[PDB]
Amino acid sequence: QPMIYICGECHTENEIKSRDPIRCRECGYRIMYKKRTKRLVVFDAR
Amino acid sequence: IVNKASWERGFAHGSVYKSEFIDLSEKIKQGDSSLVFGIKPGDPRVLQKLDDDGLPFIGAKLQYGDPYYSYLNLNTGESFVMYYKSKENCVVDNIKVCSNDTGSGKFKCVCITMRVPRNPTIGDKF
Amino acid sequence: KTALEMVQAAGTDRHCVTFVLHEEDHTLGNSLRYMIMKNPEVEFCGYTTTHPSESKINLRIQTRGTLPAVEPFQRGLNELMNVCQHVLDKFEASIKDYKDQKASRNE
Amino acid sequence: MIIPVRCFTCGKIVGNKWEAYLGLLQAEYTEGDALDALGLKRYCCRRMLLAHVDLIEKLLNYAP
Amino acid sequence: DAWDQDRFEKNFRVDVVHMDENSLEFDMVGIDAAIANAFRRILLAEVPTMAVEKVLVYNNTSIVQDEILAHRLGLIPIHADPRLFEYRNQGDEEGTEIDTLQFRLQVRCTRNPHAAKDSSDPNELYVNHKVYTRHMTWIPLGNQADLFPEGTIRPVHDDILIAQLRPGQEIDLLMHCVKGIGKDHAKFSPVATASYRLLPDITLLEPVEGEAAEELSRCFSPGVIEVQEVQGKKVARVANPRLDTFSREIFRNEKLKKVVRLARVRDHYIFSVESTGVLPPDVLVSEAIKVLMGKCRRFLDELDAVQMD
Ligand SMILES: [Zn+2]
Ligand SMILES: [Zn+2]
């Protein structure tokens, strides 16, 4: 899949490919966070 | 003197949140302004350490000398890389992608926010 | 890989030797110091931790009347084992006499 | 932020005494009787649960 | 004086006062401070337990972080018996049946459809919004399903608030319990706190009467000085000097700091061993007595290996 990004105010999973204007494709708010996926990070309990 | 068991249980544990605002036309500037964050498919520098779009993963621990962002001049294809040049161990916390004030800016601004744990070591002041 | 060193006074004197007990602290060296001082063939038994960042104790055993200091050290180890075995026995026989009155009183 | 699992001074599990302490203060106990009746007798254990600002009911309001 | 062993096997006695689940209070009459402190200091830092060491996250989309969650999981008492397990040998991240345990904390949080009209009580609005320690699925590995019953490897308390979630927000981690003593890290300590105190003796050097006995009864802790009538006057006597908190409030009073001799009784300790629940407190004290013996065995073994003759 492409990398999911999340808008700050309306929360739509927008898939920003590397060649477009960055904006949310529902409301148009410009700050867009990045979605956390499954990968293994090992933390010690100390 | 601080009790060591009490330190190990959570006495004055904290964090410190470094946040680096990265732009690819205010800092890096050669020509044509076509610098978007991106990877070339098959780069050994960024293999399984950065995501498929050039930014790091979220929750990914970073150390000194790890890949930190990789961006792609679209005119030729010559993807660069930049390395994490800080001492302390940091965890990538959230990554916000910022456009310009209109909403038609190209994918060249980002602001990586990073946790650094920073517990009481010896030499920290109360 | 061993965890006891013995440091003589002058390479010849065997009455004074400072036992370096690796991987200990004041848990053992305060109770060894209690037992060896109950031996009348000891002029001096004291201990010190070398530095708190380290993990060993120095144990000066200093014997009068012509004995090596391995014998008050061995006697003070067995004589502490024979304290703990007896404390273990009178503790496992008073837990049992407490469970055998909690249960067999009204139940 | 959230209640610590153990008291800092002595390692007593006090991390299970936050909901059953709000439940005693909502049911009209005084705090000098809602800590003895949870079995917190030392003033380092009482300290952890008396002076605790549970600052995650204020921090989850900013949620996606 | 020398060490008469039959003076120790004649004037030593353990008097258990109160023992229940996860607590113990007893005496040790006739033992000096250097062995009593050794028992206390082996209960706190040398009797070993099992505790969470490695955490393997995937999608911690929670407000409680990836680091504070791992530290918070490490401080959770795990009800596996330590003596069945070995120390994990060093430099081995992957574990086997002998060394490690594994759990899994997989909790998603989703909105509640039913029973949610015009209310705001959070239990009625969300499902799985308080990640408690009863959400830890034990994932048995190797052949540990046969050594242990169904439902023995377990967190001790099952009511500990790990995190607090909202919809969308997820915890999906995997843990690795290891064995250690309470000197490597204090999440391994099996005791709340183990401590001793001497037994007080309060001695009335002068017969108190009348209005001073009720004054004397409030200078000590409630329970110590009873004030009962003996032919018209209210005399005072000692009764349970064990209860006295030794606060010395009678030495603030000028008329009655000459009618008590508040001191202690030599070598009459009162322990108190409160467990965190991993082991009962009568096996923690026995496995604290049996570690001082092993520390004494190891050095005699070293001396036997050093001298040959
Ligand atoms: Zn939007
Ligand atoms: Zn406490």
Image (cartoon, coloured by chain):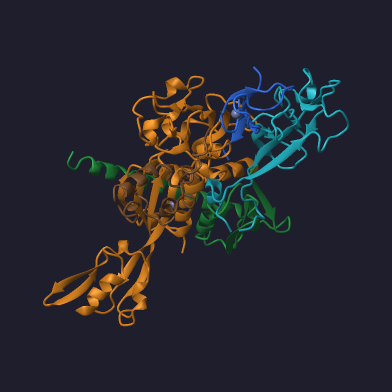
Which residue sits at x=23%, y=74%? E214
In the figure, the brown chain has which letter? D
In the figure, the orange chain has which letter? E
For residue C59, which quarter of the picture? bottom right
Residue E116 seen from this side: yes
Q: Where does the image place residue E217, in percent across and percent down from the top left?
A: 26, 71
Q: Where does the image place residue E185, in percent across and percent down from the top left?
A: 55, 43
Q: Where does the image place residue B79, in percent across and percent down from the top left?
A: 82, 24
Against E169, residue C93 (above or below) is: below
Which residue sits at x=56%, y=35%? E53
Q: Residue furthest left?
A: E231
Q: Chain C is drawn in which colour?
A: green
* Closest to the observer, E174 or B118: B118
Q: Chain A is drawn in which colour?
A: blue
* Closest to the observer, B126 or B110: B110
* Closest to the observer, D58 or E261: D58
Q: Where does the image place residue A41, in percent across and percent down from the top left?
A: 62, 29
Question: Quarter for ligand 1?
Answer: top right
For residue B41, which quarter of the picture? top right
